[PDB]
Amino acid sequence: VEVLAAVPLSEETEFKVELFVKPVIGNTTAAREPTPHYWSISSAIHDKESGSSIKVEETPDADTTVCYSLAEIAPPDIDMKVWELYRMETELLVVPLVNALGNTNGVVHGLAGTQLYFWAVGGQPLDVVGVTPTDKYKGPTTYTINPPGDPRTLHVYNSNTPKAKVTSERYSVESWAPDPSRNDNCRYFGRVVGGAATPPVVSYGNNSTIPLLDENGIGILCLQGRLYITCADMLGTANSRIHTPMARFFRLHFRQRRVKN
Amino acid sequence: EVLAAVPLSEETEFKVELFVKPVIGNTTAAQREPTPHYWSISSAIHDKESGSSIKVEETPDADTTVCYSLAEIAPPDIPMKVWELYRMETELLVVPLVNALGNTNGVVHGLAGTQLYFWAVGGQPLDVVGVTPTDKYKGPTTYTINPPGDPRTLHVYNSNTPKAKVTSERYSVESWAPDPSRNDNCRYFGRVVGGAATPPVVSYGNNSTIPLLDENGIGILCLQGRLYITCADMLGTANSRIHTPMARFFRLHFRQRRVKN
Amino acid sequence: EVLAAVPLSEETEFKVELFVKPVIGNTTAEPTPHYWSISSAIHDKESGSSIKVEETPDADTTVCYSLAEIAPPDIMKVWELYRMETELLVVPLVNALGNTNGVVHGLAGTQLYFWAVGGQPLDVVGVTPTDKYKGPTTYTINPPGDPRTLHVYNSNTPKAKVTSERYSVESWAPDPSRNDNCRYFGRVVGGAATPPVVSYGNNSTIPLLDENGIGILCLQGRLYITCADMLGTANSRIHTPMARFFRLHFRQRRVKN
Amino acid sequence: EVLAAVPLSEETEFKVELFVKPVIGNTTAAQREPTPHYWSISSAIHDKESGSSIKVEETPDADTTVCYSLAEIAPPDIPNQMKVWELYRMETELLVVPLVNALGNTNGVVHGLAGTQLYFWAVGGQPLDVVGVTPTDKYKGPTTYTINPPGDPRTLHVYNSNTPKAKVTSERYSVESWAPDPSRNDNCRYFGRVVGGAATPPVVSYGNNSTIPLLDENGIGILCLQGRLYITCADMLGTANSRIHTPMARFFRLHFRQRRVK
Amino acid sequence: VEVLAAVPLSEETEFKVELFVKPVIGNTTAGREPTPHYWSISSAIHDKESGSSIKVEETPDADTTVCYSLAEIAPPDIPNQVSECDMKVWELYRMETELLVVPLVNALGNTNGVVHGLAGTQLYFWAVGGQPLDVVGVTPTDKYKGPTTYTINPPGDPRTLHVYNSNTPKAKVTSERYSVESWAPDPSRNDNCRYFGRVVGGAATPPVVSYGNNSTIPLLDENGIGILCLQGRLYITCADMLGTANSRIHTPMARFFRLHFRQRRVKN
């Protein structure tokens, strides 16, 4: 895989797509592939009944976790030419939450808490690394693909850390992190904010682009004719339910790249 | 489409200053179009008497929501040349709120909470997208144009998400977000801050401009001889009432653009 | 009509340093400003009283814009303010605030940081924060009009020039539609418990040239400084910096006719 | 009377590193120079035993206030000078560790350091020019150790003609009573940040690959006209369990070249 | 010693390594070298039983403190390393470092449906050097001794160590036993070393961590010289603390490094 020069940006050598990627929340019902919930509001987080021996901090309902969202783009068909993602815009679809959250005797409720803002854009699926937040965290007993291994040994990156590729919408954001040792031909960016009551701050607009060229001036190459978008966003909780943007918008700019073959 | 800019001359330039008033929903039914409240302080958010079946978190009073504000500018006739907005300044009209908020045994009350800061500037009305914050949010039963559809399916961007254009001051800021897939010939910018007690931070001054040229050096073109200003700003709540800046100021700079016809 | 700058010479340059004092309203019977950096306590009146403190507070508990004028030496040619430094005079408040059983009290709350510099007084716009806010019954020049109609900028919005130290910062905001030949900058921070953050130093300047390279022109031979700063409250009293420092740099400008 | 810089040479350059200790007031009284406490943790702030007439918000124990720290540097003599030493750049860096276990807990609830903060340094060819101020209409300062601003506290909470001036020539100037004088301090660089609030988290960065240039608009640094450089500084991170905390030290590395003068 | 010119970037003269450095928490159990816990979650901080005399704010369990993590890199041996006039040595000229982190929500539990969060006092620190990190011994309190096992505590009276003075002990981070609450990097030393640290106080302060894969940190000094591996080794030392949750300290799952070496000429 040797990279040559960019093709002169022409009408039939350029390609643009806009798309909205929906947020994903886990599904407790068992089906045939499990179905994602496209929700921007989860079920309530709460300790189970007195008698029950399910510990919600160890095995939460799939209902109350966010998984990475997925989308694939196959640009039109074309000493070899391949599609190159050289820039993009991405923007969050978001409204302020006030009235919908209710009030306690006129004290307005608000959206706040632990947050994630993540996007990834690559010529193959996102390489991910399996982790536990706690010595006792197993994940949901349905829907989610949980990291294989003893939770007591996975709260640190070690030789037994499991690796995986985000090829379905079943990877919980609380259990899998992007693998910085892999993800070649891929740009990603993530921001985690902790705290129980941390206000989320989101900006959006329509006159701002993200360049995607590396140190050599090479963007993402679609070597198998596909671009893999993977992303996840979490704004905090409100009334014990996790909230998400209504969507993550992408506009992708492709040119053509010469590759030796 | 677009040719060269006309040499900046006295006859070929045009400037306007204006203040855009904030909009709050009106509970009284009209006689005639519904009338906006130009208020920077809403009615109190509070639950109904425990007998009542109106759920304020599902159908709030129009009284307690902010809608997008509107203004149109028609620059003077031209004796095809078209008006082009190439830069502007916009500034919030704001004072600190201290004494007016009262106190509790000398404990000074403050303005804080969930915030929005938004402006848009375009050759046509703002393209907007209909959304729900909750699986149960319907919006006010009067005044507001609410997003058509089942609230259970609108909390995520999907094939059923309704589209609209902000052509009246009846679009609640809690239900409609700018459409990033549209809004060509338009620049907008939005910031949303969550939280129930988040302090607002506003800066203002008179020596700062916003350039409005795109990647090609083209500003907003008034193809039908009009510029559409649409904006909304929310600073938080105080004593259960939402506050807004007293106004949003704009100064618009137009030159003339030669256009192939 | 503005011409070229005069070559920077010894007699064509002028510098002044000054401290501008904060202003708090005065309840007693021109009315005299209180030059205080700490106000009276905000509290409701006794139960019997018909005075509503959120509608008509004591002048005692509000900050008004501070004023200073500078007339550079006599010299056609006119004095031009082309740069300045401004800096807040400030100390951390710890012991002075007291404590509740060892829990140290702090300064926090709603803030304003504002300065303006112009060849005429600051153009200001009258506003109400509430449908019911009238302002203090003495000292302050309150915005004329029904409070129910002034919480939004409209036709009834009164205009005024800051020509005395009686303009409450809670009722008057700089007019962005006017204030030609003037730079100003303001920051407002809300919240009841918001920590103030203030930086200061002595190696930082603010340029004051506009898009044309023209600073503030003293067309009537005067420079008008107007400013106000509020750090929050402590024990129900509003605090201010001890002063706002300015150093002004003037050159000469040829103004045609 | 400033001329050109001397060509950077081995003999014409000079570097020093030093740690400046934080200063807290000392209650044990005078007769003789009072002794500073070099502490990064003060005594507890608390009201006196009920019935007492000492008001801690008006006259606190010297124990519970931070004073400006001092250090002087005299670079080596200049074989037949007039050439003078010029501080043209420096690095300064806070010596700091996160406080967790040491702060204790309340039924498993970890205590933290938070509160009102100051971060200040000054570097000059003479002592720091300072201005006397009161935070309150009733604040007198500690009845021992500290040099308190002269005047009625009711008239000192604003800068006016009654504002006393002083030079930081001892480690007895309380940070709560004296602020750098922006109308003076020629041949001096200083920088200060004040953060209010009772529970404000401090944020401190440090590293070893970052310098602060000290040249003014003319390309002139601090000139040691009497052969000395005066370092004055103070840093406060907040409180923990009613005691004020400080960095363990403020580090400086100073870079001198020589400046020719007439 | 006397640094000469960089060797022309070649295939033969370049070297890259990626590695993950594990966080370190103290170990209470006990003969040989004490074993670090590679945990991103500590034991609970709690006072002892009302009948005990161990004061947890003076001598905490090794269990509840973070120590500096260590890693060493020895790049490949150099062909024709020494000549008449000079020798070639490995020079670290840039790196990327990135935290391995996930949001903690469900794992933290809840009280009546009020979701728990990770918050509190934080440290973000990395160091990269041709020798071990020079560190300075300090006390946060006039009474803090540190854990009675595992940790190498600063020698001296705690009453005199809460300030930098002539009694301040110096040390090199040569094992994973230096508690982050007792030892700070020495700015008066650490030549041929770049380090960077951020401390955030407060009991309830939210941590904010960014990560990505298109950002590098240059490591050249004022002269254009990076870290020189004069004894053929690069020493990585680092520590990161995100706050507490349910009385236990949390850490990133790891700190990732990618190191870029070229060759540097040096007069012997």
Image: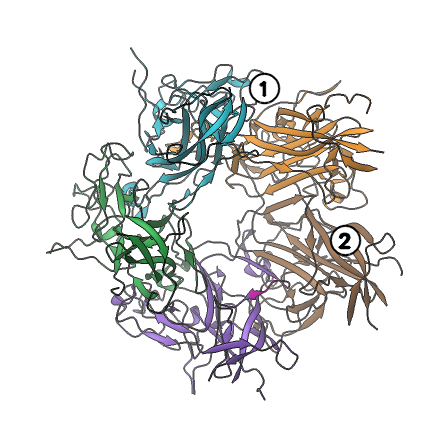
Chain colours: A green, B purple, C brown, D orange, E cyan
Q: Which chain carries label 2?
A: C
In screen coordinates, is B246 left or right of E71?
A: right
> Where the C terminus of chain D falls, by quadrant?
top right
- Look at the image and say whether residue B206 sits in the magenta stretch: yes
Report which quarter residue E55 is drawn in: top left
Among the 4 quarters of the image, the one containing residue A160:
top left
The amino acid marked with disc number 2 is: Leu
On the question of residue C143 being in view, the answer is yes
The one of C72 and C93 positioned closer to us in this rendering: C72
Left or right: E21 as drawn, with respect to E221: left
Characterize the local packing of mark 1: few (<14), some (14-19) or many (20 or more) Cα atoms within 10 angstroms.
Answer: some
- Stretch of the chain drawn in magenta: B205-210
Relative to C60, say whether E145 is above or below. Answer: above
Vertical relation: D216 (above or below) B209: above
Relative image position of residue A211 (x, y in whole percent): 42, 55
SS at mark 1?
Answer: loop
Q: What residue did someone put label 1 on? A: E165
The residue furthest top is E31
Residue in the picture at 59% in, 65% down: B209
- The spot of residue A223 in percent (x, y) is 26, 54
Looking at this view, is B85 or C130 the one in front?
Answer: B85
The image quadrant where one finds the N terminus of chain D is top right
- Give the labeled residue for mark 2: C248
Picture layout, residue A91 above or below residue A61: below
